[PDB]
Image (cartoon, rainbow, N blue to C red):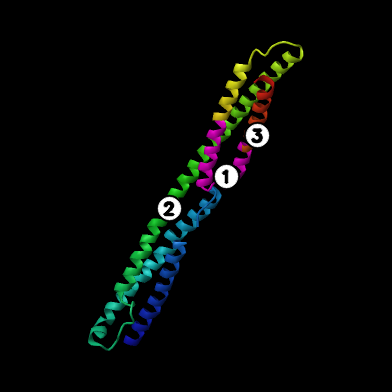
Amino acid sequence: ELQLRWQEYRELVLLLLQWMRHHTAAFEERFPSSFEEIEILWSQFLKFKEMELPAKEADKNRSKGIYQSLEGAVQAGQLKVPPGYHPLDVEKEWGKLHVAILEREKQLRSEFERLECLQRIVTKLQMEAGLCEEQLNQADALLQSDVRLLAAGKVPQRAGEVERDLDKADSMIRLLFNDVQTLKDGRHPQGEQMYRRVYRLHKRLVAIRTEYNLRLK
């Protein structure tokens, strides 16, 4: 009877408190590097929030109801509640879990918009790199027409333009290195890859500038 409600309540509150503690910690811990990852995190999150959380809400409120039946005995002294076993301590710990659910929903959305932001930059960077590469091709080809003029004892006619092209490619390469640092910071998983393709653009630039300095300067 009394001993039975009491056992139901303690059993019920013991597990409840463990499941709350477990899940509040679980959250306090997990940053996706991909959309693939975030999809899984969000699915596990919605599963918990929609499938699991409502069962435990039912258990919580059930335990409350069981407690008011026992309340005559608690106040009378016959039953004593272990610290943190009162409906009011279940509630505190439930409030916390609830806050941790809201934070995590916030973080997941913010991570998703971060990934979307890092992808705009990847497109930008890749777009700018093909342009930069074209700009290197234009400078390198102006150079050879000048170098082939010289081999037939004729003067360079585009020296001013080649120098311009390299100044432009140099500006582009510095934009690219910055895009890369913005990815690195954003913890894009390939920040270091993208750095090397830009680094390769820089070496092309240093090789073409060098040759222009010896040959036309």
- In percent of the image, x 32 and y 69: which residue is there? 92
Where residue 89 sits, quadrant-wise, is bottom left
The residue identified by callout 3 is 203
- In percent of the image, x 48 and y 41: which residue is there? 117
- In percent of the image, x 40 and y 79: which residue is there? 11
Separation (CA) of disc 2 from disc 1 = 22 Å
Disc number lying in front (2 or 1): 1
| Residue 1 visible at all | no
Separation (CA) of disc 3 from disc 1 = 19 Å
**Helix, strand or loop at disc 1?**
helix
The residue identified by callout 1 is 191
* 34 within the magenta span: no
* 194 within the magenta span: yes
Disc number lying in front (3 or 1): 3
Boundaries of the magenta span: 172-198
Q: Are marks 3 and 1 in contact (CB under 8 Å)?
A: no
Disc number lying in front (3 or 2): 3
The residue identified by callout 2 is 107
Q: Are marks 3 and 2 in contact (CB under 8 Å)?
A: no
Q: Earlier in the sequence, mark 3 or mark 1?
A: 1
Which one is in front, 137 or 165? Answer: 165
Q: Amino acid at mark 3?
A: Lys
Which one is in front, 171 or 19? Answer: 171
Farthest right residue in view:
152
